[PDB]
Image (cartoon, rainbow, N blue to C red):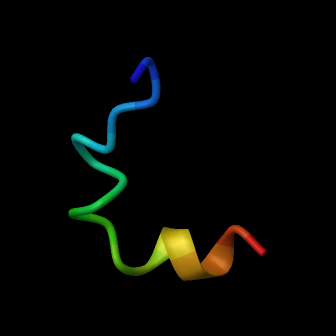
Amino acid sequence: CFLPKLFAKITKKNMAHIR
């Protein structure tokens, strides 16, 4: 709900780098 992925879904790099 309050956690949109406007850029969370478009990002396929830093995402898999977060952890």
Looking at the image, residue 9 lies above or below residue 4: below
Q: Classify residue 19 as left or right of residue 17.
A: right
Q: Residue at x 32, y 44 (%)?
A: 5
The image position of residue 6, as x and y in percent, is 22, 40
Quarter of the rendering containing residue 16: bottom right
Q: Residue at x 78, y 75 (%)?
A: 19
Quarter of the rendering containing residue 1: top left
Pick the front one: 10 or 1: 1
Q: Classify residue 6 as left or right of residue 1.
A: left
Q: Classify residue 3 as left or right of residue 6.
A: right
Looking at the image, residue 12 lies above or below residue 1: below
Total count of labels: 0
Residue at the far front: name it: 1
Q: Residue at x 27, y 48 (%)?
A: 7
Q: Classify residue 18 as left or right of residue 5.
A: right
Looking at the image, residue 14 lies above or below residue 2: below
Residue at the far right: name it: 19
The image position of residue 15, as x and y in percent, is 52, 70
Residue at the far top: name it: 2
Q: Residue at x 34, y 33 (%)?
A: 4
The image position of residue 10, as x and y in percent, is 21, 63
Looking at the image, residue 15 lies above or below residue 5: below
